[PDB]
Image: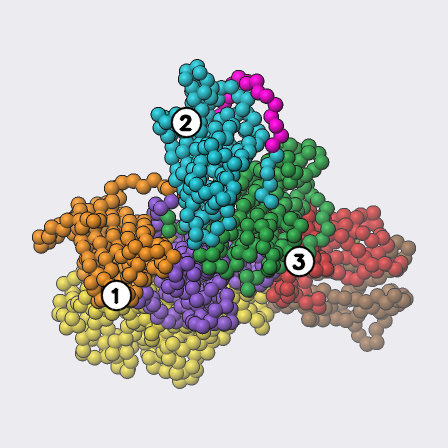
Chain colours: A red, B yellow, C brown, D purple, E orange, F green, G cyan
Amino acid sequence: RMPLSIGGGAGATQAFLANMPNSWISMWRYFRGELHFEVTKMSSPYIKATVTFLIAFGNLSDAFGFYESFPHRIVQFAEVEEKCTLVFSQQEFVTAWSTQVNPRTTLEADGCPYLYAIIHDSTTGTISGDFNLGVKLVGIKDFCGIGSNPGIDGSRLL
Amino acid sequence: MEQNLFALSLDDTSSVRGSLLDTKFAQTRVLLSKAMAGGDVLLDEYLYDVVNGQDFRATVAFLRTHVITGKIKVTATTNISDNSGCCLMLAINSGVRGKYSTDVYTICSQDSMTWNPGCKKNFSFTFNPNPCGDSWSAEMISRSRVRMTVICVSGWTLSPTTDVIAKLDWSIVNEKCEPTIYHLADCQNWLPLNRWMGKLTFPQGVTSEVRRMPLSIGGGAGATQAFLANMPNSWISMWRYFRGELHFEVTKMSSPYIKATVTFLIAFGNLSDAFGFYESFPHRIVQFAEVEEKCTLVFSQQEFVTAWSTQVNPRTTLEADGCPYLYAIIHDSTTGTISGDFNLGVKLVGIKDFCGIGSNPGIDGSRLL
Amino acid sequence: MEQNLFALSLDDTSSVRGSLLDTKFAQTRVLLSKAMAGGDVLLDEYLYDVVNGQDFRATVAFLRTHVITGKIKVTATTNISDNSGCCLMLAINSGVRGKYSTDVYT
Amino acid sequence: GPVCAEASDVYSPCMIASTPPAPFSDVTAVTFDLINGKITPVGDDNWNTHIYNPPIMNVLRTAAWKSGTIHVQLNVRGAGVKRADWDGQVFVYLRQSMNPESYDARTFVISQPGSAMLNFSFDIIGPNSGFEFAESPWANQTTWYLECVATNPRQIQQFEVNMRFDPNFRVAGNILMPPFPLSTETPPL
Amino acid sequence: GPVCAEASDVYSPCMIASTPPAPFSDVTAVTFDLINGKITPVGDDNWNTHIYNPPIMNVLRTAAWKSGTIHVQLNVRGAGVKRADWDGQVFVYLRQSMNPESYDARTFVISQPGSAMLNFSFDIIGPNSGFEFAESPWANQTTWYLECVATNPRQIQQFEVNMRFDPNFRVAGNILMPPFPLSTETPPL
Amino acid sequence: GPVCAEASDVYSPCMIASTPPAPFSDVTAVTFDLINGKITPVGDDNWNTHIYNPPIMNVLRTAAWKSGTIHVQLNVRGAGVKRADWDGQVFVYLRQSMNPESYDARTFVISQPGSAMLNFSFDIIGPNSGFEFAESPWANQTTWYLECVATNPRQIQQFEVNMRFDPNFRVAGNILMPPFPLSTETPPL
Amino acid sequence: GPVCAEASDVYSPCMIASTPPAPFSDVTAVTFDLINGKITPVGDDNWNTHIYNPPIMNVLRTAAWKSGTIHVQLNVRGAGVKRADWDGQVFVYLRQSMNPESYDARTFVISQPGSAMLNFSFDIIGPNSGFEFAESPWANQTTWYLECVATNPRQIQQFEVNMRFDPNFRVAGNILMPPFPLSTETPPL
């Protein structure tokens, strides 16, 4: 579960890391837009798995058996393929959400959307290794920033 | 054989739609005891919960569609013999807080549907659970706590021999969602208020009854050393004086066996119940056929010579109240071969060509509804 | 307000259709042991049972539509490193009787 | 500038809090929930408090979704103290949450004998369509808090919060509230 | 801001009230009926009061229906007190009615040694055609009251109410009044 | 002018410094590097200091090139001192460099009992394309320093620097920074 | 008005004068020649004085003909005196000549404990083409003098003159000047 309330930065030990672009979007209290993500296959091509990406809320359980009842995409990489691009349109979000949520906000209480990465079948390989994916929010199209953010210190762990 | 799964139509981001059969997401059973009374809360819970143990054609779609674009439609089914009646109300409000009031007055401002099972054998209406916009979603109305309350606004004139059950059907329809936003413009051509004016109860008899409802509707409905208010009523209170064409809805809440002819007019607080010439004023005469339950009164701008106060001091005596009143008078007498009072529900639906004048510093409290 | 309920579209007698998202009725998990052998029956059960604990968009429609007119589509997902392989088969037969043979041939 | 700048408009009195009675004398604070209409002293209550029912206060408490600007005026009334002995100070903090992780949205610091007036505006803008539902668990929405610190409760007597809607205010949806107690304005004498 | 903001226009002195003489010393208040021209102390009179007859005051007292803006300036003159001992405060309340159920339309709180000036405007707008007849039993119309609380009648000596019509002022109809007593402005010495 | 001018917008608290504890009492000063976010007392530290992480502060510390206007508000909170004994003064100096050869870009001089607020703006404009990289050895670029002199550390307690970006602010490029320590706002009590 | 009006722009420190050391204590005055850059106390010197070399000061001293507006800000820093004992006053006089026959062009009168700021502008407009050559014997041209009177040199410590050119400033011709001595800004501590 990756949270879309991306304000602040990446969590660290009693500290947080931030960069100019992330700090910039934090200026806004609420935000919304079409999100563009880039998924990179960082593991050897021998490790295979089918992941399905979707947008849902923090309170679904890992055991929830019907993630594919939501609009979603299914990703599989051919041997030589390493990148994939997900675009979540404005029709996947009903309203804007908070740029940042209080760090102590429990999953069951987080009212903002999350990008979900789920394993459709199982990870396999005739070699040992984990299936590692890199995920990056490239940018937002039709970005809309709403209100001034007074700020919250800190950010959940990346 | 092998396909590019990324290409399939799995990311179908569209709202739910189809026949009423495919577009239904839940049903609800509300029990009307054979002795319900009026004030009786029959079912009150969050709208979202209505979708709980449901297993209809659109249940999953309702829950898994991120942006739903159509309106919710509720259909109620129930019916009693023609010698009985009562008045039920299904209401929707964006939220609740605390030990809230569930009085008709308090709950009917946002979206309500109100009928009499002795006159209608089913009743439906559509609503947008998100007043600021044109779309909503199950997750949204859940987290934002939208309430659905059903109450008995007036009880059975004559009890059914058994407890009765009303079946609610919830479906998503293809009407478009629209906001109902309030703003501070002194002149607006339609200010929807849905402000409950009261329940008129006329006892059967050769006696003369006069009911006076004040048009200085600021504040709210009176209560014991307290008052009740709702967003629309509070909003119109922002203005010091007001004026406009008033639109009222009168509902026949008693059994169709209890008959009376009421005459409605606009006059001042100081006429006596014994005044014998109310029909020397411009007025309307209302009579309901067996199957009729609603009536609409429109009092044009030509019935009011100037604007009046939005609110008057609570201690203002009738003889000293200088603002107009809606009067409900019995033209002949209330009768019936069955015992029962003749009960009417009255609601100021809205004002056309509304005109708000000046800022109201405010007065604490309101006369009794 | 009051409507003629007999007139509404409640008697909608049509087959299920829509995007693949809205048209899905069930998913099944079949386990391939790391030592499966060939002859190995991985899953064998009545087609209908496939729809059991399901809660997808077309599950109710699949069960409550009297005459379904489209075809069933099965999609299988799984994949191994290029130095391995095997051969799986999903089959449909109108019935079974007795202690039936589940050989590829049969 | 002996010459006074002309004030105008109607600002109605919403909520008022008076400092703990003698001999209480530590620095104490009370925080107003400007939008839901709630007063909360820091635990050493006997901060005698009140919430009034002017029109604006009833709209704020029944209106589900809000969008617009609110104009505030803090009136500070003090005990009768020789100017020469005055040492009181009020520290004002406008914030969207009381969690310690949240930062202030605006901060004022006044200090003048007897009485003082502070004017500022702030505006409600949310995720619904520029509309915000005070603290709805929904988009992890929020409210507006006004924390006031009386540095000497024996010199600073009470805080009066006056508010007024800007013409751009808009509201949508209703909230089922319990009855509102009559709360007539405590007179000045 | 040592630099003074330029004042202008003609504001004529309407009514003035001076606090009860020594040894009176409780908090006391007087309330002006800005529109009908009436002064009313709280019962502990010997609040020596006066109403003058400048043009604006005669229009206000004979004009039946009024519509427009009135610009006010409250001048507060004090007794001669060592600044270091000053403890006085004036609390000002502009309201449309004196019933306790009515809320204030605007509230000011000043506190400065010797003298102080307060400027604010307010505007008359009624049901007749934006016209209002002060307290006519008609649409339960109202008037405009200015309540002033002197917190130390021994330091705060008198309240002077100065008014001026905005150019948008309009008036209609006449009121039969009894003769107006000559009331020449009490000099400053 | 008893009447207060309306303040608005969201100014978030960036950095705060409190004077050396008793019995320290010489004139002392602390200087803020408004742009890189650094506090530096004059050597007689125990000027307890803090840097917060509001959005603006993180943009300022990671944004390589900056161009635009910054709106500042200095809040000065004082110890609790009888007004009659107050002698404190704060001298404020805004400059682009601390070398003695550089002259001040702007200088303020305040002196009022207890608390005081100072508001001023300044704007970043450099050689890159109106963009400036704080103290880059490149075009011998510079930063913006705010030096504050507390004339009596026993009466003037702390300096709070509040900032806000003007809508015309622009930024470009990123700076690799070490992690930012959590620094929750020290409460007022 | 607790709320501070936002200051802006870059005003650089031009010349500064500090009152005669103790036990000197008569009313004393110093006069600045704002345009030629000269400080002149009244004879009882030991008014320690300084002239700085910020850009504006070098343009003023080498530019032969000038035409335009100059924005000034007088900062007054005082000795550390209990507010209750403060009796100091500064009288400011802007004039075009020191002959007694000439009248003042503008006069200010401030009096506030410790520190005070005075802002005013004035503009150079001459006979050449709206251009003026400070005190050229030519059309009997003139300069601009700022006379400051410290009423209690033991309470009022120094006068700092800050200036800034309005964008409409224009200059023409050069004046052969002797070298300018380095004059780095005396620090605040």
Q: Please tell me the numbered disc located at residue E24.
A: 1
Q: Amino acid at mark 1?
A: Phe
Residue B204 against residue F25 in the figure, above or below: below
- 3D distance between C-alphas at marks 3 and 1: 60 Å
Q: Nearer the viewer, residue A6 or E31?
A: E31
Q: Nearer the viewer, residue F111 or A87?
A: F111
Asked whether the residues under marks 2 and 1 belong to the same chain, the reply is no
Quadrant (top left, top right, bottom left, bottom right) of the C terminus of chain C: bottom right
Residue found at the very far front of the displayed protein: G23
Residue F170, image x, y percentages = 60, 40
Marks counted in the figure total 3
The residue that disc 2 covers is: G98
Q: Nearer the viewer, mark 3 or mark 1?
A: 1
Residue at x 25% of width, y 52% of height:
E160
Q: Chain of mark 2?
A: G
Q: Please tell me the numbered disc located at residue F182.
A: 3
Q: Is residue A103 magenta?
A: no
Circle 3: is it few (<14), some (14-19), or many (20+) Cα within 10 Å? some
Residue at x 32% of width, y 65% of height:
D188
Residue D109, image x, y percentages = 49, 55
Dot 2: element: loop
- 3D distance between C-alphas at marks 3 and 2: 62 Å
The dominant secondary structure in magenta is: loop
Residue B362, image x, y percentages = 32, 61
Circle 2: is it few (<14), some (14-19), or many (20+) Cα within 10 Å? some
